[PDB]
Each structure stands twice: as C-alpha cells, then as structure tokens.
Image (tube, rainbow, N blue to C red):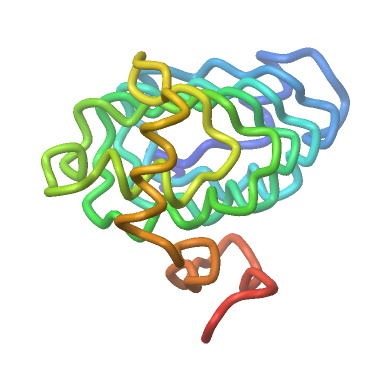
Length: 161
C-alpha cells in the first residue's frame, strides 16, 4: 500500500540524519516514486535528485526554500502550471525537467524561465541574460499566478487567486 510512496524511514536510512528537516542532499533516482509528500518538512533540502520516477505533482516542493538544484528528468509532469510551485524558490538556480511531457509544449522553456526568477540553468543549458529578458517579455506575470492546488503545501502567499 506504500508502493511508490517515499517514506521517512527510507529517507532517514539513506541520509543518516535524525529528522526530515536535517536532510540537505537527497538522491532517490529510479525509485518508482509517485508520492513525495514526506518532503513537506524538508526545509533544509538543497540538492534533490528525483529523476526517473513517476512524479506528476510538485506542490510539496513549495516547502523547500533552500532548494538550489532540482533534478526531475524523466518523470510524468503533464501540466506546465506545476512549475509555478517553484516560482517562490529564491535559491533555485539549476532545474532539469527533460523528458517530462511538458518539455514538448510550446514555449515550455520560456514559461519555466519566466516562472522561476532565480534560475540560472534549465535542462543542462545555462540561461543567458537576454534569454531571461525575452522570456519575461513573453510571459510577464507568472510570479503572480496561483500554483495548482496540492495536498502537500498550503496556498502560496502573494498570488492572484
């Protein structure tokens, strides 16, 4: 019944710390994961690798203000608006979403850049100053857009709702 659910036990076995709040780096690639709600308390997580899982819903990551690098290659993210859960991540400089369905949506790269103001690199390609400027011209308001509802975060503050 916990098939696909990341558990506290598995995280703490792997990382050797006493609480989810003390997890700073976590690599759980290729673990058949579809539920990562346990990360709601991962307030100190900085480097997170979740590639090659079954994830479609990113709301738990609103609880991770320290996130610096986030690897999500080859998941099941189907809705571009899931990336709005990363809009308020002030320290997130590296993101990979390659091989999720959204990567083939028109204007995916511009949307992600315009949504995540801190980002310096997306999908293994650094974001140039002029690339960011152009993304904001196309999509000027994404930091104000409410992210989708989630079981695993409260509604983000400072959004049009």
